[PDB]
Length: 124
Length: 124
Length: 124
Length: 48
Image (cartoon, rainbow over all chains, first blue to last red; front, side):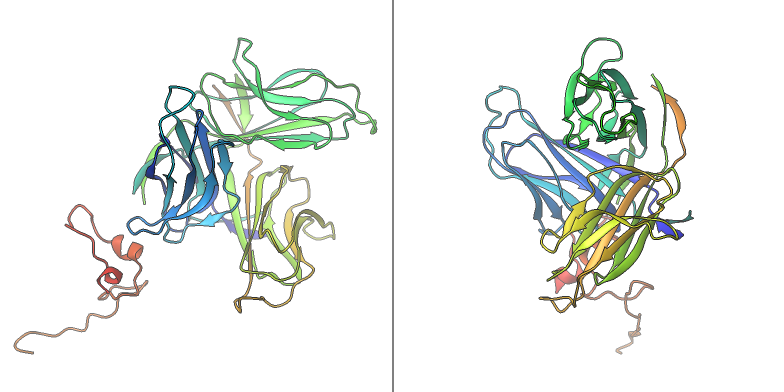
């Protein structure tokens, strides 16, 4: 029994304030082993969607991987990802107005747990 | 592309024996990045609930975040947490009698995967 | 507040080509803290199941823990595991023919995030 | 040619260095640009 495993893991946490726009949340290296993406809505939104996905450092390669309507206020991507030139995790809010029902601004927190491309050899 | 990430991660595993009471399972530092809480029931319970949640080191600030009835015997919190003075993960069992249907005592295992508040700067 | 935690974590990624057989994907040490098992299907299968589970290094102790039909193409185990002599994560495909609807062979990727049995003492 | 040495510098591949071409991905090319020295980014695919 012998294998190569990723021994280095990072967590990136980034906040944005949940109104229309595009935000570049997490930067990933080539060969990164993205194993968890979680999005959370802190507050009480009244209308809008948040779409998180992957895009290039420069060019317009955005593609949503997780969509969150107002109601559930939390989500996790159902899929695991190896970074292949799509080195930006990004989130866009197309519909959103002011906070709503609270008076206090609505937050969105994205946490990305990913393993670095480096590998080491271990036998058990 | 440059960011700060959490590079240190710990897993805490703690067992309790699934009968009425309150148990202080996992201790977390301020600023800890709790990214997974999982609860497991080893055995065949007959009646009761397990509620895991957060509470203070001293004062009575308990609030359940995951409730487990008898049937499913396993659960994971659907939400991610940054530790803000609620530095105890705790579990309470309000209803439970002896093991039931087995003759062998019923176990509960809680695993908490969390990232330390420390950050480092990386560019990709 | 003082405890012992697992401070060492590895990720093992292994690919197989999604046709009938048994594959030994990930090797785990005794006392390993398996906290995530994820299976992914890259391509468009037409018929078949993938069952991942645990088995011995030698003897025929296979037992499925996650079954994936054709449609959903992704899955994650709902349960957390401490390795007790079942030191092989294995995957079997009982039904599968050629790629189907694509012309390009169908891949399956398994990622196992597990914490090493070593512990260290920390107080917060 | 016209007093100007013509040099075959090779092809930029994933292994050794040569002149680029439109097969190099935008990320792979841009990794070698300082972004603090360049005025603008035009990659070989963008030029194509």
